[PDB]
Image 1: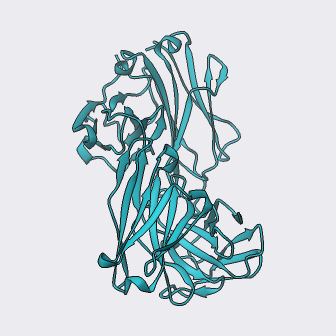
Image 2 (image 1 turned 120 degrees about the vertical axis):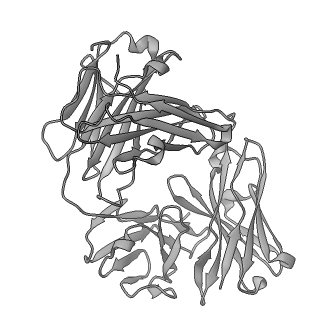
Image 3 (image 1 turned 180 degrees about the vertical axis):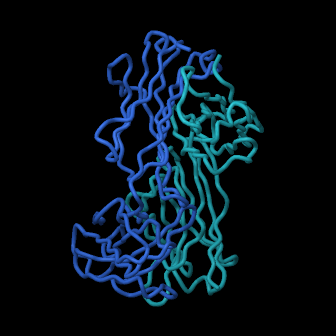
Length: 214
Length: 220
């Protein structure tokens, strides 16, 4: 099976900038390569086919080239509506295959996350569960590290993270980290902490609380 | 113009089978092959196979041999794809597509059909209001939360104050655990207006015909 590898999972650009995405085939596929654009909730859209030809209706800012194993897709001058996921594909071999995609995102000034921690709701405890939630909102870039600490010890078991896509309004990212334990275990620890590490600061942003302390 | 209309979403259990349709219009059905593509959660695209309308001849991705069956009804210019012995691994959006110009493959796409495979039973969500830490928070802005846990199937519609608050809201993608979904949402308000100006989390789950409200209240 021929593997198509794209240059990046994410790429940051600015309106008016020139951007290029590349793809490498694990085997020679001549010029049987296509490039697609896909927006959330929509089907992929063909932009470039046979490595270098624009499909009907595709704007001149989109071009591509390559033959063999190395291909390039270029947007000469990025427009706001071009922020999306781009995929390359090869149809020389069988089965035809797609790359994993490259998400083109918008660059903006760095922003530290706003961190908030939340002890389990009283209602959840009555059911025997204990979820501690930590929100890390509106930060940039997307790169971030969150670690939980219970009474000073790092905890990784029972933690689930969820991320929102780059916001269309302020170009920031947000994340939710949830540490779930049973009520029984939650009631055997005192201090709960969620600390975030982001490039915007050498020091971690720490949010904590002590169980039953009001 | 060329159009490919696919059938609605389906939700079934492991071991089941499903048959979806792709109605072609705007051209002579038998003039082009119909390809099918699978896209799983993370947006991973995979080719399933293709069918030649005129003869019914088929070509499959070895990976999906015996799992997918392609057929056509020339009479109604419709292509069908049937999946059998379903498992959670088959959950994904399935697309039908057609080529354009000359050699311009995948020039036209259907809107896709969502297929969800799970053994889970319909379960209404437990909705938990998350007020700030008992100790205190700083600044004039504060963030509140709402945890929606243990529901099935997707989706749920979460709003704050019945939709009156939206600007400072972040509703995160749901996570599947032990066959059940969980999601969280946060809302950030300004000018020390909480708890003076009430905030409530509302959650609707049509599959269970439920609608619940949870007012956020200071911890006492």
